[PDB]
Image 1: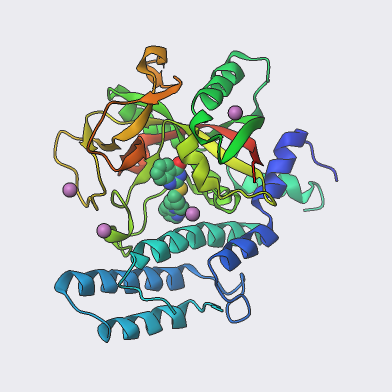
Image 2: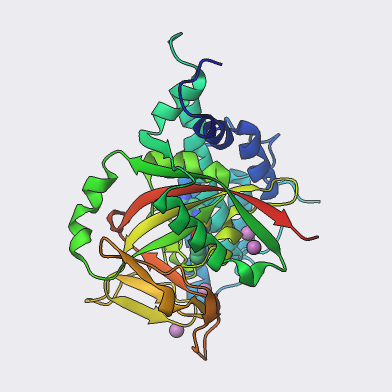
Length: 345
Ligand SMILES: O=c1[nH]c(SCCN2CCN(c3ccccn3)CC2)nc2ccccc12
Ligand code: NI
Ligand code: NI
Ligand code: NI
Ligand code: NI
């Protein structure tokens, strides 16, 4: 076409505005595209589906079973039709499974709505400007690239049995107004550069609107550590959320500066609705952590790029560290990585 963006940026645009990718994500969740295509998807419907799951949360809280639920599930599946070859919403933590789907549908709705929004510019540049984000290619021979590559290589070996990783492209990203929304928290201590993985169908929403919290109608019990923004300090953890496969091996993971401050440290799931005061975030303690001996500090921001070693933390259910903040202003996105996954099987 007639694009003036660098070639890696053009490919990223085509990747995140891929409507076929959006449909496959919905099919992956067994949503019936015939009864509800990508065009029919709406925020008010996702909002009402969230609230239905919140009714199941109250119902499970008050202690009921199997005839309140089937009605609540019949309501859920009527609003969002599925195509099975109808599981119980009150068992096997299905509230979490459905609430993650709604999270991804919210981003897929934003991507599709943005895509349907002059002769001068190639549609690639038109869609790029809709993100209201400045994306520049990081030179592979730069100091930034070497730090980021080392961060990747040091924190993915523990999953080599599942897959290997190769950094294709590194982008520096600057969301419009995010540096301004984050400025108050740069005074907070304990700021770290952390990973956030996601499917490619989520990043049109991530770039245009930043990382968000689940809406108020979302069930707090649908999130392992409450309705917040989740980060990891090892790509082995965040890369799992790209949902790449051998037939879809290219994933996206971002690096973001997170103001953690005083961390409420936990060793198992806790559907937090409010933090204790003095605490600014949650840190789920994992069995594996980057070697603190290799931690480097950057403009007062810690980069825990050490090789994965055992943390010595017994009595924990988490394999990797988790970091959750509950204010969207506590996050400043800085880098976006394009990664090729090489699977063993
Ligand atoms: O690195 C990690 N990545 C992800 S992604 C989890 C799924 N995403 C879906 C989209 N979503 C929202 C939010 C608000 C509004 C619309 N969508 C946020 C949730 N979880 C992680 C969890 C633990 C550690 C690292 C990670
Ligand atoms: Ni490797
Ligand atoms: Ni629970
Ligand atoms: Ni999954
Ligand atoms: Ni507990």
